[PDB]
Image: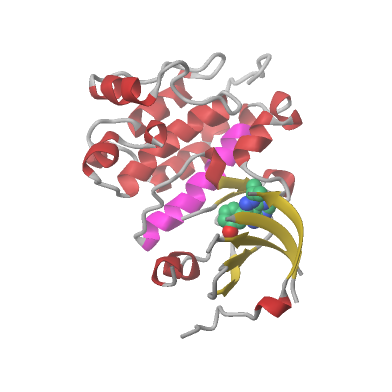
Amino acid sequence: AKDAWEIPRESLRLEVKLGQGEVWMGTWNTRVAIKTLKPFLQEAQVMKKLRHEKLVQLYAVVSEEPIYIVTEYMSKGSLLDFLKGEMGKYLRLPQLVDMAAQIASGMAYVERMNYVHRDLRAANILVGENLVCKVADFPIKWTAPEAALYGRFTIKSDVWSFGILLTELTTKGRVPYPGMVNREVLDQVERGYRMPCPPECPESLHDLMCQCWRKDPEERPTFEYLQAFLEDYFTSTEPQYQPGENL
Ligand SMILES: CC(C)n1nc(-c2cccc(O)c2)c2c(N)ncnc21
């Protein structure tokens, strides 16, 4: 049965509840997060095969119900909470582009590795100290049309979501497509609609969103492209950038 990721439940001290399965902060045998699932192995092979700096790191599993997935602790919760908290009003484009870059990097690794995330959006990004961001957790509004309608999930659909994630970052956590219910979105993105440029955000960054929301999966950029473009941004793209009232 068990593989070398197995640890005994006894080695874990659950302490702070973080959200309700459930997520607890804890101790081993080392501060850790434990995801717990309300009463499986094959579909956990994903997180065990992928080790990288900008992806939340797996530490161990308890493969007996109730199942415990144990990972590194991300001191600042979801990117979505972080954007919506006290920190929101102090964030600007430098910080937000940089966060976007780290995510793109984790993702570009997933790309090399030949995997697909499937649920990429700020709720599944985790923030540590010093604005470290890490991809976690391997719905229509964040989904590419071909995936929402025909099940065609590929790294290209992940790219689509990334483009939506950039509106979350640049609106400091706002739900995409303000005012539309799901049906209206699916109907409208099919008719060709796309979110306009967020207030105070450079046209060049909204242009990058639009390449991500190209109707042809194959024509959307690579994450490796996104990673570099975001890394090089305030030199190669907006050298004249000045801080606004919000970005
Ligand atoms: C935001 C939420 C309570 N949370 N989920 C976490 C996890 C998210 C996704 C999968 C996990 O196994 C655990 C997490 C963490 N590792 N550190 C701190 N907070 C965390």
Residue 56 seen by the camera: no
Query: Which x, y percent locates residue 24?
Result: 69, 57
Q: Which image quadrant is residue 180 in?
A: top left
Query: Which x, y percent locates residue 187?
Result: 27, 22
Residue at the image position 55 percent from the left and 41 percent from the top: 123
Image height of 55 relative to 98, above or below: below
Depth order, front residue of 72/112: 72
Query: Which x, y percent locates residue 163?
Result: 42, 33
Residue at the image position 48 percent from the left and 45 percent from the top: 104
Residue 97 on the magenta segment:
yes
Question: The C terminus appears in which quarter of the rendering?
Answer: top right
Main secondary structure found in the magenta portion: helix
Image height of 202 relative to 13, above or below: above
Image height of 235 relative to 194, above or below: below
Highlighted magenta segment, given as a residue range = 95-113
Q: Residue furthest front?
A: 39
Residue at the image position 25 percent from the left and 46 percent from the top: 151
